[PDB]
Amino acid sequence: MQIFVKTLTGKTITLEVEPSDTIENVKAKIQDKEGIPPDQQRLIFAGKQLEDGRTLSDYNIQKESTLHLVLRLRGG
């Protein structure tokens, strides 16, 4: 699905991929396109963070509808 990804800088990004894809797979399309090692980035979703491995579908989301995610910076 077209998962939305908004950054604190407003930089929006759209990734079209089957929710069964892994999480580290997504962070990949980002890390390369932004060149920001996930180390200095932490994702926030509904008050919970995403763990490595496992997929979005495999996690069994409740709404399974439009998934909204927002990337955050490390430190400040």
Image (cartoon, rainbow, N blue to C red):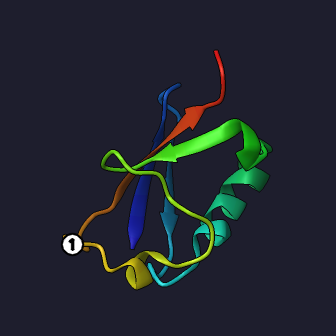
Work out whether residue 43 or residue 6 is closer to the camera in this orientation and state it.
Answer: 43
Image vertical order of residue 69 relative to residue 76, above or below: below
Q: Is residue 24 left or right of residue 10?
A: right
Q: Is residue 34 left or right of residue 70?
A: right
Name the outermost residue toward the left: 63
Which quadrant is home to the N terminus? bottom left
Q: Residue at x 49, y 28 (%)?
A: 8
Image vertical order of residue 65 relative to residue 5, above or below: below
Residue 37 locus on image (x, y percent) = 78, 46
**Amino acid at the residue labelled 1:** Gln
Q: Is residue 7 left or right of residue 48?
A: right
Name the quadrant containing residue 29.
bottom right
Residue 27 locus on image (x, y percent) = 65, 59
Q: Is residue 59 left or right of residue 7?
A: left
Q: Residues within 10 Å of mark 1 (few under 14, many from 20)?
A: few
Q: Residue at x 40, y 77 (%)?
A: 59
Q: Residue at x 39, y 82 (%)?
A: 57
Count how many numbered circles sit on residues in the image: 1
Residue 47 locus on image (x, y percent) = 33, 45
Name the quadrant containing residue 54.
bottom right
Residue 19 locus on image (x, y percent) = 44, 78
Name the outermost residue toward the top: 76
Which quadrant is home to the C terminus? top right
Secondary structure under the numbered disc 1 in the rendered image? loop
Residue that badge 1 annotates: 62
Image vertical order of residue 51 relative to residue 8, above or below: below
Work out whether residue 9 or residue 69 is closer to the camera in this orientation and state it.
Answer: 69
